[PDB]
Image 1 (cartoon, rainbow over the protein chains, first blue to last red):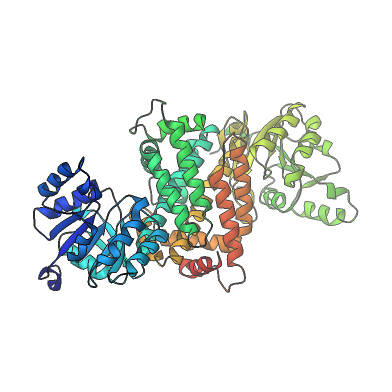
Image 2 (cartoon, rainbow over the protein chains, first blue to last red; image 1 turned 90 degrees about the horizontal axis):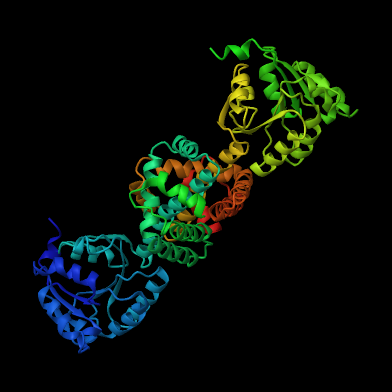
Length: 299
Length: 299
């Protein structure tokens, strides 16, 4: 019950980058022959990695391309490379895209870099759609939530959703998808940071339960102890990667001509708290009753 | 159905400071002759203010005291003076308190200053209880929520609650009541600040409604649009005074040996946003749909 125009259509996808994320995505698509798959990777040319990578390409039913120019055949090019390589990749692909083709940039970079990738693509004939991957890929494969933005975002979402992928078009302006992903971090990690600051303060003052009561009375819809349990355990376990996500978010907001003091302070806070909790005999299972006394003392 | 020990008891209260807050409190107590009331004020000695202040003392049924030494008669002394005068007041009263008397400091100062007030009182015979007034006094009079902390906090709460006041004992340690008041600000104004940062960012990126959706999905208990309506209108109207409350909260947290980056960033944010919104034709009634585009542009 997806779109007819898109089911009765010749659909070739080329990955740029054939790492884990690209592999799991191509994994879930491969058995269906939902589309002719291909992948360009530099390691396809490295004698030390070539054999092992080409076998896996064969095992997931993806064709290895020897060169970037092998993407000329694709309707949709997916760019999943190391963040640092984003622009370089874009610039390589640009001359080889057909004028109907869409390059979707799925890299973990801010709207600024996305804009430069879009610019490289524009020096050739292809279209650019900006994407942002909303979850880790392994647990979801090809149904990982992706946000897309651009002239052709609705069009590619529909086309790739007809193949079983999980895209939503969030705007016509490239930059909007990574902006949305980054800003969404601000509320979520901002709240986590506020709990860290309020609760460890409260704890040093001996009024923790009373302060949880007072937040519970002010914002009654949520169970704030469940919130503090959940998000402080997130600081415990993934504090390092949560600080990266925050650092990027501050840069995104700054990139819009806005000061980002909440995002910067939250990043600092989550990093300080993660450090504070390491090697203290805590468990992700321990709750705020567990974490807060440690943070109180260690901060 | 309050305590018998406290109803069948000789109960004299002396205010130090006879301003609005002290007047409204003494107002609601005065008609009942719930207690022998008195008040020391410097203006009781100023020919320019004396007549007018003594008439109002008579109208609310409070006795003027010519001197601080007139508090020797009180069981409970209430200190409501300008923040700056807190310690000075405490030091004046200390020699005059009886050894059964309780000095309750109700001034808008942090636990640090409260501790110094407590120290002055300790150089005499009286007891010290630390209080913190939780709302503006005019709309509540004598039933304004007060938090108290100290050895005798339970005792004074019960005694003053037997006279119709609205006290809760929150701890045995002086400093806890103002700590609790201040820290409670962190979550509340932190959230307001996070909405300002997230929403005006989102708005510059054209994804405001989507970001509200994504906060609504993450923290489903609350209606986040009502939250943003409510708290941004608070930034509009009372942004100036909300920044003071935040500045104090950062100092309180700092006073505990903790860095206060969330509190400091929130204070900055609320002040920046309040400034941004002034003289833009906005109304407290306007909601986030109204405020956010203004903040987006003006920040």
